[PDB]
Image 1: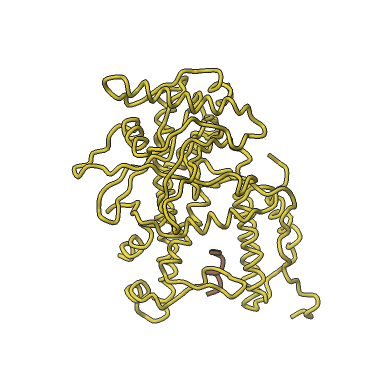
Image 2: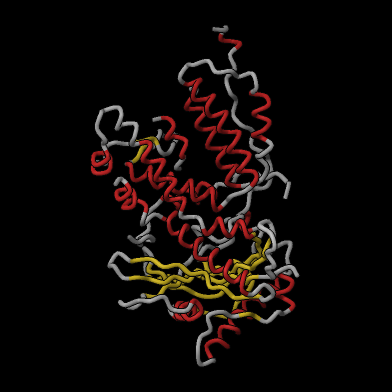
Length: 10
Length: 422
């Protein structure tokens, strides 16, 4: 389940 | 630095309770079925109606249509008759010498009814996420033809979200041109896209048809009604809630070479009345901005490791798929993926914001951004002002009613929050 917000947690 | 117990820890957003949310896109997405023809080597776009008839001839299982899931708030016989009417008019086109560029349909009582001459809360259904995931994947076809721009393009060209861009530019352009040229007439518009196959050949794709209603679009805001009629292999009985706005017919039997062998599966037609506007059509026509925009987003993420290591690591990041960003979230753990996944995830977000554009999304975006900044500052231990969290949660949560994409975005935020302020 892809969630674009997880890119904020790099 | 105030005492801990006084510090405000943002709570999850509250998503409304209700019956599951329903599909509200202008056309089908993951459930779409293409009937396709291989264009000649020379190619040269034929006439939509000619291609559409050609595409329909590639299917060999057509049968007498029947209603298998009614539109609860509709006159379902009118939908069946509307479909039969489309076939009759295609037959008439077939019988003339030349294929015409456009076809105006007879204004029968069923078409006038269907062309027409929601504040109740809904809970978030899992179909929305499933849609988003499918938009992120790669198709076997490339939907775009021809810096860091080049490596970006390699990754998104076969991306399902990019099919949706091209589908939406085509339909909205047909729909707009028909709207200008034939304001009174019920015009029959094939839903067509074009792609290039793995082998290199051009392909023309028929998803179905749209009948345009009356279109005196004096203003941007003025609405044109239309009936959409779209092939699919999705049985509506799997997820009835998704299809509340639709009448679904069974129109055919399709052969699939399955993992056991050759199966017969029913082909369906998803039918519904829907609306759009001059401004909404023009925005549909602009959907290629979604590629420029997500490009800007990726170039900016590659302008962080370009001013950190004093040398742009583009050839690195793209050429080496060993670097990863956090992309998904299995309760197993945070799923990570190559820069390709990131490019596609971001495209899909940009596209879905276009496809599911709404006032709710406008509110949600403007407000959730401010809370997002607070959450980032909290996570960096920076002590941002939380004095207006009350007003902010109100401004956000009054946008959480029934729109499936907003609901999904809210649900995504709540997951981010848990991980961010763990």
